[PDB]
Amino acid sequence: ADISRADALALLATQELDSIIKPETSGSAALAAFRSIRMSAGTVSMPVLAA
Amino acid sequence: LPTAGWVTDDTSGAATGTKPTSKVSWTGKNLVAEEIAVIVPVHENTIADSR
Image 1 (spheres, each protein chain N blue to C red):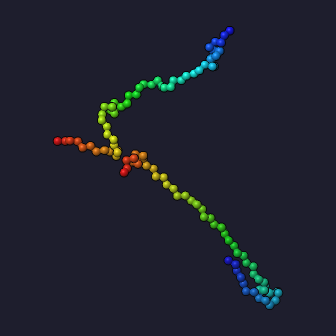
Image 2 (image 1 turned 45 degrees about the vertical axis):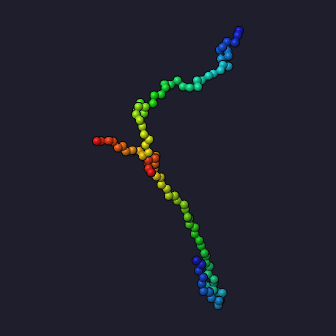
Image 3 (image 1 turned 180 degrees about the vertical axis):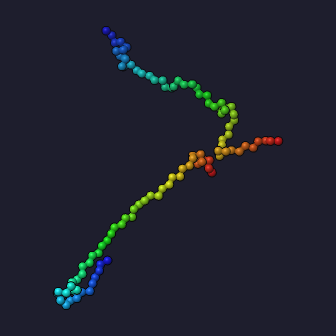
């Protein structure tokens, strides 16, 4: 006769990970590669050299 | 409105010797509150992009 682990199972401490198992996030390849501008109007204008 | 009459004073038997009865009367009416309403919906991007 002895205190098995099952006999004391209800006394054992518990632990949950403090973080989630997930992939590291990529972000947009477009936002990573191409330079961007802050817009204030919804339809910005863009002069382009022609000649 | 009340109504008055001319009365005689000659004899107790004359019907024209009796003072006429009259009433006054009143009526109620109600001032009832009623509601004017309108809703003006707009897109949040319209509010964001307007000057």
